[PDB]
Length: 221
Ligand SMILES: [Cl-]
Ligand SMILES: [Cl-]
Image (cartoon, rainbow, N blue to C red; front, side, top):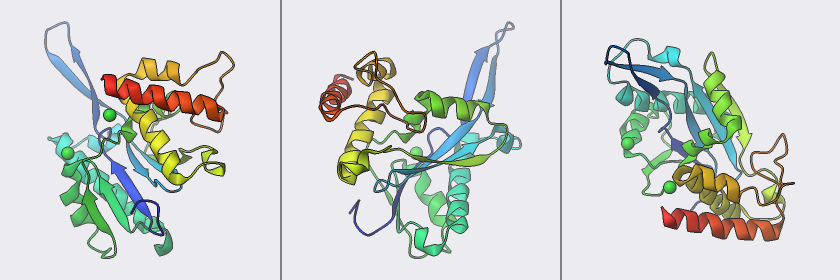
C-alpha cells in the first residue's frame, strides 16, 4: 500500500489557520491570525512540501476555520498543477475528515487521484515545534513553498518503512510532550543536528534507545 510503485501524499491542514488570543486591559478578547502551514508529505521518499500560509490570505471572511480547509485543498491542487504528471500523487491521504469534500471538489480534473481518510495519528504539524520550521513560518512575509527531506540520510541504511516509523514516533512524541522528546533526542552533550538535516546525527544503537523511549513517552500520554 504505502511504499510500493505508487506516489502517496499525506496532507495535514491542522496548522493552516492559527491565531493568538489575548485578554485586553478592557477585558475583551482580541484574536489575531498568525502565519500557518500546510504539510504535504511523501512517506516513501521523505519529501515534505511545506506551504507557508501568510496571514494576508485571511483578510475578507468569517469562519476562517472552515475556509482554511478549502484554502488547503486549493493549494494542494495548485501544487499538483505545477508538477509534471509523472510526479503527481496517485493517492492523497488525510487524517482530518474535514479535508475530504474540499479536496474532492478541487481535484475533479485529476480522475486518477484517489482521496481517502485515515484514523492514523500523524501529527505532521508538530514540525512547528522544531525551531527550523517554527521560525521560518513565524517570520514569513508572504506565501511560499519550501521543500525538505524529513528522513535526512536515513534511507542510505534503512528502508522507507523503517524511516516512516521513526519519523512518526518523533512527531507524535513532540506532539504529546515537546520538552521531554527534545531531551530524548539529545542523548549526549556532543549530539548535533547537521545544518542541512532536520534530526540529530545518532548511531544505530542510539536510535534503538531513542525509538523505545519515544514510544514509551507516547504511551505515557
Ligand atoms: Cl477535520
Ligand atoms: Cl499523537
